[PDB]
Image (cartoon, coloured by chain):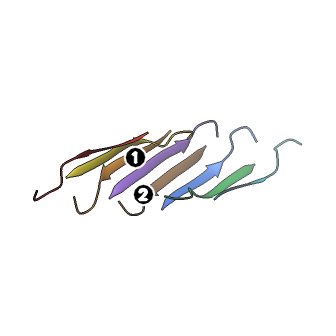
Chain colours: A green, B blue, C brown, D purple, E orange, F yellow, G red, H cyan
Amino acid sequence: KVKVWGSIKGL
Amino acid sequence: KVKVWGSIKGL
Amino acid sequence: KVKVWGSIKGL
Amino acid sequence: KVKVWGSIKGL
Amino acid sequence: KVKVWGSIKGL
Amino acid sequence: KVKVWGSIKGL
Amino acid sequence: KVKVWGSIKGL
Amino acid sequence: KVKVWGSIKGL
């Protein structure tokens, strides 16, 4: 399992 | 703010 | 599947 | 207010 | 695909 | 009223 | 691509 | 910033 998390820079 | 989440399919 | 959700800051 | 939603293609 | 929808505040 | 819509390139 | 369109309210 | 982490299933 490869998880992804975050927020898009500049938005 | 634009959040991003989940998992990479196939991994 | 990597979902995305939010709003554009400043708009 | 500008909504952002969806998923990252390929993930 | 990451969609965007709204209006510019104040305008 | 000033609408904003579309999709973020590369996503 | 994120498009923007309308008119400034009150003007 | 959108972080990615985990391990590949089956390996």
Labels 2 and 1 within one chain: no
Image quarter of the C terminus of chain B: top right
Is the residue marked by circle 1 packed among few (<14), some (14-19), or many (20+) residues within 10 Å?
many
- Give the SS element for disc 2: loop
Q: Position of residue B3 (x, y in %)?
A: 53, 58
State yes or no: discs 2 and 1 in contact (Cβ < 8 Å): yes
Using the image, determine if residue E10 lies above or below residue E7: below
Is F7 on the left-hand or right-hand side of B6?
left
Q: Position of residue F10 (x, y in %)?
A: 57, 39
Q: Amino acid at mark 1?
A: Val
Q: Position of residue G7 (x, y in %)?
A: 18, 49
- Kindly identify which residue carries mark 2: C8
Q: Looking at the image, which is closer to me, B5 or F10?
A: F10
Q: Amino acid at mark 2?
A: Ile
Residue at the extreme left of the image, as rendered: G10
**Residue drawn at point x = 42 percent, y = 57 percent:** C8
Residue B7 numbered mark, or none:
none
Q: Position of residue C3 (x, y in %)?
A: 54, 48
- Kindly identify which residue carries mark 1: E4
**Residue drawn at point x = 61 percent, y = 43 percent:** C1
Residues under labels 2 and 1: Cα distance? 8 Å
Mark count: 2
Is G10 on the left-hand or right-hand side of D11?
left
- Give the SS element for disc 1: strand
Q: Looking at the image, which is closer to me, A7 or A11?
A: A11
Residue at the extreme front of the image, as rendered: G11
